[PDB]
Amino acid sequence: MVRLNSQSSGSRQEGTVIRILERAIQRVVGTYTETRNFGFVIPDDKKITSDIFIPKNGKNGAAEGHKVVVKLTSYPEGRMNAEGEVETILGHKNDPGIDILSVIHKHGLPG
RNA sequence: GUUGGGCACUCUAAGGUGACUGCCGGUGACAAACCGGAGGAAGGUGGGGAUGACGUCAAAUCAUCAUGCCCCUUAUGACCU
């Protein structure tokens, strides 16, 4: 429910997400990465500019390499990132036929 | 500890050790790096000091000191109260 601004530093009208009327992106696919004694799945697409906090109870295989879908169990909060889990361990990200299989789960195609 | 009590511990102070990308994951030219993880007292330029290049102001100092040219030289020297 983006609101207008009474300014514009360009040719475009300035929106501002004063509120989110609806949540979409229910789930993301990505590579899981171990950080500072933690986990963080990086979304397949770069359109999500943040990572997804993985707690250990939602690691479920995902190591440095493994591709996994995330049933996002929480979402960003001001400065904080989205939390999640690990769904399907698609396989090591650098595998021939993951490129397809990654897209198979990205789009939410049948199986 | 006051005393007996090796002296352990703390300390005292000489000599060594120790830290680096050395290591293990990512990431990335397989390298470098970057990002984390170990282990360690110490994490990625360990921390404080010390130690620089050519220069300028005819900068300041003839009251630190010395000093050419002067000046004083029974006094501009010197002594006391």
Image: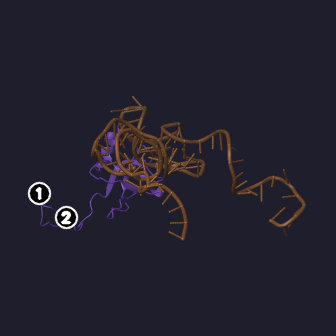
Chain colours: A purple, B brown
Give residue B41's position: percent from left, percent from top: 58, 52
Q: Is residue A2 above or below residue A89?
A: below
The residue sitting at 31% across, 58% down in the picture is A26
Q: Residue A46 at x, y = what percent? A: 28, 48
In the displayed structure image, the side of residue A70 where residue B5 appears, left or right: right
Residue that sits furthest to the left in the current view: A11
Name the residue located 26 percent from the left edge and 60 percent from the top edge.
Answer: A24
Q: Quadrant of residue B74?
A: bottom left
Who is closer to the viewer here, B23 or A54? B23
The chain letter for the residue carrying disc 2 is: A
Q: Amino acid at mark 2?
A: Thr
Instruction: Give how far across and how far down residue B20 sits, in percent.
Output: 50, 40
Residue highlighted by disc 1? A12
Q: Position of residue A8 (x, y in %)?
A: 12, 61
Residue shown at 44% from the left, 50% from the top: A35
The label shown at residue A16 is 2
- Is residue A60 among the parts visible in the rendering? no
Give the quarter of the figure containing the N terminus of chain A: bottom left
Q: Are marks 1 and 2 on the same chain?
A: yes
For mark 2, give the secondary structure. Answer: loop
